[PDB]
Image (cartoon, rainbow, N blue to C red; front, side):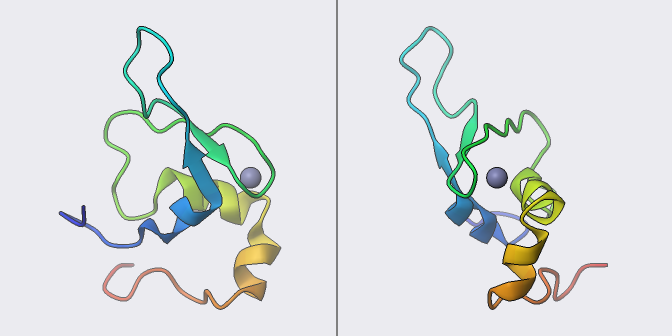
Length: 76
Ligand SMILES: [Zn+2]
């Protein structure tokens, strides 16, 4: 849920895989844009969802093209 920062829209370009193993689920994220895994880990939800970084890293054109201008109304 939205406890702290806001902007979990990047998730729309990623999907969490099942645990199907000893390690608890929600360990990695599968990019629905290209299909690359993007882990997060501790201390990640600090505004710019680790995902975003990947989206603007390669999908920079996708973000700009889409109706997504700025992702920080009260952040700099
Ligand atoms: Zn990707």
